[PDB]
Image (cartoon, rainbow, N blue to C red; front, side, top):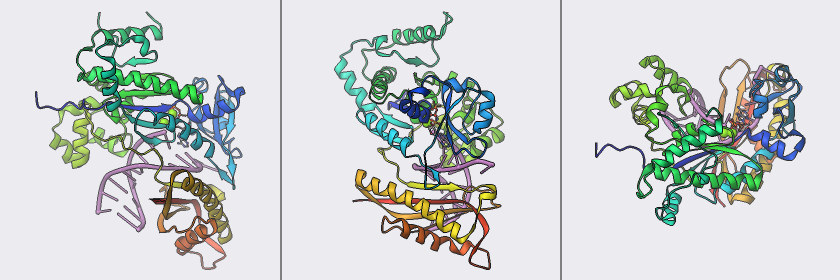
Length: 430
DNA sequence: ATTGTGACGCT
DNA sequence: AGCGTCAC
Ligand SMILES: Nc1ncnc2c1ncn2[C@H]1C[C@H](O)[C@@H](COP(=O)(O)NP(=O)(O)OP(=O)(O)O)O1
Ligand SMILES: [Mg+2]
Ligand SMILES: [Mg+2]
């Protein structure tokens, strides 16, 4: 009772841009705005691969990983924007620079952890304490939360979406104990006010819309964020967790979407997150290891301790290209030319990074895939990165991988290569 | 013939 | 260090 921790010590938000690469292209080209449209990589094979889809186009069934020719079968009027190509490969610079725009705005409000090109976690605990003392016990108006959903509400004793949203918000606000600056539900609510302000600033200053989750930890904030995408934010309280988890498939929780989550389902004979509460911590550790078992025991109760790391910049800078089917690289000149292409893009990005961010990479990772291997990477080897020079970097990468050529004659490369990858890592201040 | 990223865990 | 998992 009194000594049972409840995981209500922090306020954590997760901000995720809505159809991000699409919004970047729609900002640039107004003809694409408010249309079914998608962003595509390459074009020659089946029209190119779709990597981002506007919500208008999703209504027709268009998804990421679809070929554009097939997407056009579902949506004949689909508009397409193409990823830029440079040195023979897709170049994501426009989206990385748009991401920096958003992350720099978010960093004005709190320390952020860059989780991907379009999402960041925010630790709002301190900002919430400050705003609470500035308030001085004043109630929180629903006008301060114009895009917020309270998960699980309304409940108890209108048929339009916005009406239900406001009904649930009213129920939440009416029950709130504003006199108590240590109430976790009040703390979440103030967190949600701040996240409204943050999202308004992102939209005002970039044109981009986003969704957000506000809860007590990263896993619940991420789950909350997706509950009412797009252009809305969702508060998941500690009290909402039993009902939310009671019908939540295990695979929806971050880190359980793969083999471990399938083994939880298989070994325990359960389907939903909340069913995990019936096992002891030792039982879960016996099946899934000490770390995973303790994590699952706490997470199915809504408790998680993973901190929002103070890290706004990526810690690796990488460049990779697949060479599928008959395009696999089969000569030494081919392998050299593409390592050079990858190394030149890497040198551009690394020089810009050193100027912007006062750091230098010190290790170069070289990874390849051979034809016939079903694994993503087939070989990874490291070497020293001492100079931001594309020819040196590509020569060094070749020296580290040259022994995997099974061919007798040097001029040929066998078995052919289906992926090349260069990654700069191990940054030091400069 | 998804592709091009990126973080972290295990041994 | 090199390999594997998981997520964008
Ligand atoms: N598998 C992949 N391969 C390449 N690029 C990808 C990718 N997945 C995502 N991207 C790129 C394209 C995406 O625009 C961007 C952000 O990924 P999301 O947040 O998962 N998807 P979005 O923001 O589009 O829609 P939503 O409103 O559901 O958040 O990363
Ligand atoms: Mg997104
Ligand atoms: Mg995202």
